[PDB]
Image 1: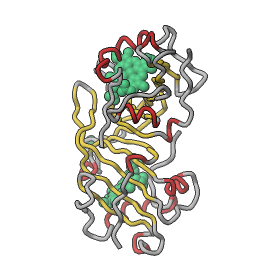
Image 2: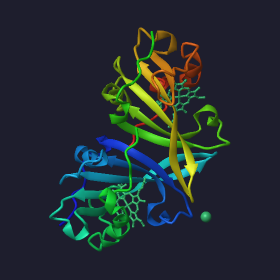
Image 3: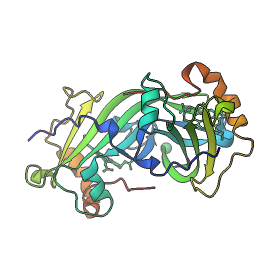
Length: 136
Length: 136
Ligand code: HEC
Ligand code: HEC
Ligand SMILES: [Zn+2]
């Protein structure tokens, strides 16, 4: 019933990035610069296949410092993790949702079995609960 | 003596990102959101190891759009490419410098043998002419 810490995700495919600045609706808790990573199984779904069990997507969130009109990556704030298991995570549409504070495996952030995460990602049911799109 | 287009670089290790906004000294021509990628040979050099011939670093530069206190990736502006060959690129410190407009292999940008690129990167001689640092 727990999402596994995605060891080695920094070596995975970089899907996209985005900056969430103060005033954004997602500033608490997702403000900063984030990078989306996908393991090989998640790439199958992002390409237009079905997401296989074992697909993992990671939302890697950094603080940033605005320094002379550059936004410079600071410390890692958290990672968000979506782990595909149609049976084990059936209550949240077949994705397990977890956060890790500072990307550390012992700093679990989700306290409601991922119902809040799922509530927002449910808007993307037609794209299998995933917002990010593959770009070249 | 030409730098090879770095085919498949989007599958490589994501080193770091930064956002360069108007007012920054580098806004022309490096304004936007950029992502740095490294092949396996360049990871050896970045890790504190030495850079083998065949190491490639890519500077992947996107225009960005402001969207309600988010900065969202737009069109690719260009890629910058550094290819390691201590002997073939000896005139520019053992790295070959090339730019590809919109990341297209047909739009090579560098006209002066990479002397302009090298003039800026030469400040980083002590880190083998590479600015980027590995992070977690
Ligand atoms: C809306 C109010 C959100 C809530 C609550 C959560 N997430 Fe989210 N997530 C959201 C958006 C708009 C995006 C896309 C960002 C982009 O760069 O386009 C995301 C993305 C993710 C990802 C990457 C995969 C994807 O769907 O694009 C993951 C792994 C992710 N989110 C996990 C996650 C977890 C674990 C949450 C509860 C702690 C969570 N999200 C809440 C919007 C929203
Ligand atoms: C100073 C005025 C620069 C000139 C001219 C060029 N580059 Fe550059 N480059 C610069 C900085 C400050 C950085 C680091 C950015 C960051 O996020 O930290 C870079 C980075 C690169 C990279 C990535 C590898 C590295 O050294 O970090 C590449 C592949 C790169 N630059 C290529 C490149 C080429 C091909 C240029 C001439 C067309 C060039 N750069 C000019 C600063 C400057
Ligand atoms: Zn506003």
